[PDB]
Length: 35
Image 1 (tube, rainbow, N blue to C red):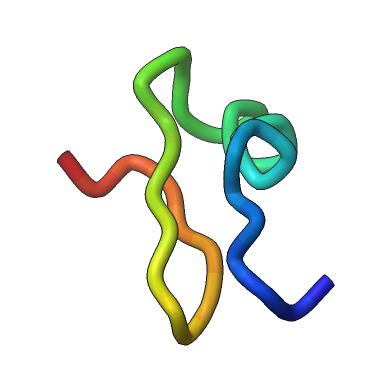
Image 2 (tube, helix red, strand yellow):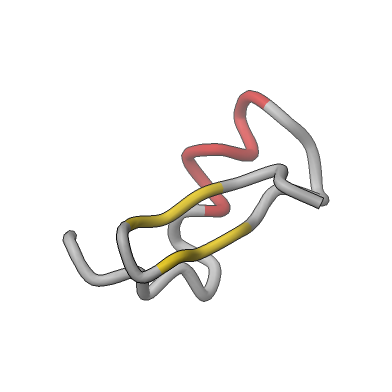
């Protein structure tokens, strides 16, 4: 798991912490709650 692909997967692990509006992706890596 090292190629962004943050189309919804990263959103699951991170959602546990944050809520629904938790998703963000950058070449370097996946991210969440950044808006």
